[PDB]
Length: 432
Ligand SMILES: O=C(O)c1ccccc1-c1c2ccc(=O)cc-2oc2cc(O)ccc12
Ligand SMILES: O=C(O)CCC(=O)C(=O)O
Ligand SMILES: [Mn+2]
Image (cartoon, rainbow, N blue to C red; front, side):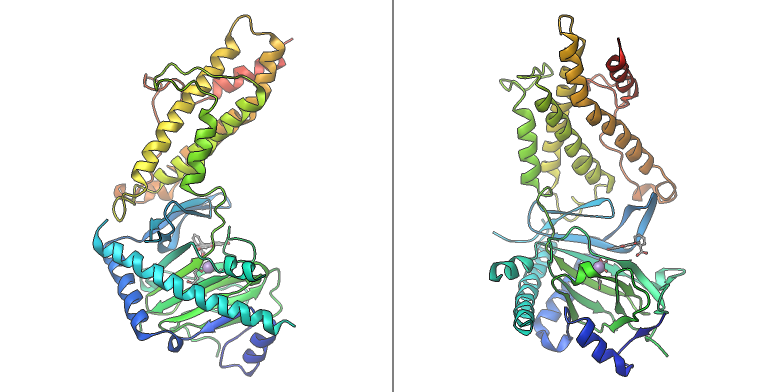
């Protein structure tokens, strides 16, 4: 395989014909004032230690990301990639003033890039021969900030198909975005084939290493845009230069099951089956109908694994730059603890003498997959909290395996390990 850069005569026509949905707006087109502001914002964020490498999970292995990052965006919004849910430090849509100022800066960059994107999307439609679709596909709700110092990496991976040289980030799609949504990236580098000292973004067609890839040089303050279905039909990578680089990558995160309001509402739905006169350990349920019980136990899993474990696995890195999620997370944990109460109440009822066996077995069938998944996912998460790299990484830089409690812990109604309970319930369902 081979690739094309601006040095190749064929670059220009290949871009024009096979990448009309890829747009580059060079530093020129962006005001010197905005450049100054976002570049300074990058630097304060970096100095206040707001960017971290994430311990992600990909095809079974636990890996530290080469880039350190932070997610900034709409209050209560989250973004899930590589099995890790990132939580926004909020930006002032309708904390220390410095970080607050930085987030404010990245909101107005967001506004600017949003405008640029709509324009580009409008011009693309005109070329191609609705109005609501365009604006919704440009309505960026988060940005993921990235930083890498390549001189800090002992060995960088070679780009494997086109001879593009050292990769800072491997070939991928930006995951979990709204369908056909645009992506906009502000790139900030500190200042035969592609120039090794300069940062590039590379593109290829999915499934395809025969059509030469493009490598687009990125100088200080250059912006690039993936429009419409480009992010889906193509992969991209980031090719490392010799100097450090920041990027701000603005996305329309698909957040239908990914906001604080969404998850609080799911919890409230679950607790509708609980007599709510008073908050104490004496949990009693309004109904034992299979469909209501299954739903309750599913919500229980959702808040435990998608929210609590995700949040705490990331070493409590937030109250550092924002306490915003601290109270929400306390609240979600209290809701989850009530639901541990619910599971116990269901279990009590299963054991009640005078419960017909047919009704018991209908209850078992309703809840068994949820409890099985709860056991398995607890194993998987506990594994993830030790692994190798978690072991290797310093004591300061370790994942927290919360919520977790000992067999002796009398504050919790059920054991953390559900193996016996699951076995027993399963056994009962095979009884004759
Ligand atoms: O880019 C990498 O090689 C990498 C290294 C360690 C951890 C994650 C990644 C990696 C990504 C890192 C950040 C990001 O925004 C996207 C990434 O996508 C990847 C896709 C892969 O197939 C394989 C790897 C990645
Ligand atoms: O920085 C870029 O150019 C794209 C960002 C990126 O590839 C990522 O880390 O998701
Ligand atoms: Mn990307």
